[PDB]
Length: 180
Ligand code: HEM
Image: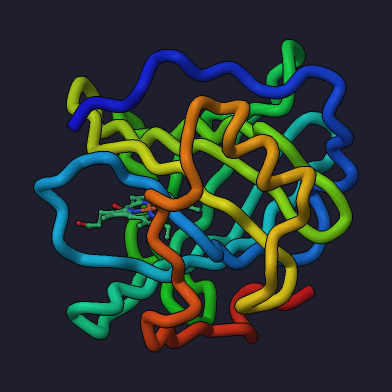
């Protein structure tokens, strides 16, 4: 299901609150009703002199499999957003497959504070949208998002009641992969 094109980042957001620690997805919204598998995800995003690089993990809770990626792209000047190319790696961060140059994801930060964040991700394989997802993020696994971030969900035109909560899925994480 094609990504929403009604996305732009929150202006004036504090990038130091976003590029910090690791994030766990506590709640995700993929509106596509053809989806069946539910995921857990965690990642650790960094930024140095305009270049964003992040280590990313997905766990397919239905199939009990996982995959790892490294994303890299430029920080937009117009707001807290980046379009990254991604490599596939193993749990030891060894490269399995270099980036396919036709593929990218755009991550747009909608809110970020010291405990929590809200972001939108659209993954593209050339001219095909793989899909988009909104993710509520916290620094501690199974934590509660802040009131500020909950407000951002509503103000994005969304309803938290429709998100899938990950705390009850039986997630397996790889905390070593996302550690400082
Ligand atoms: C719980 C939240 C998330 C869910 C439900 C989700 C879901 C998915 C799904 C279903 C796929 C396709 C898997 C496949 O068929 O191979 C995928 C791939 C991908 N996702 Fe996510 N995702 C989540 C969070 C994220 C986050 C936070 C990021 C970036 C920071 C991200 C970036 C990507 C990328 C780059 C791919 C392509 C990976 C590859 O082909 O190697 N996703 N995701």
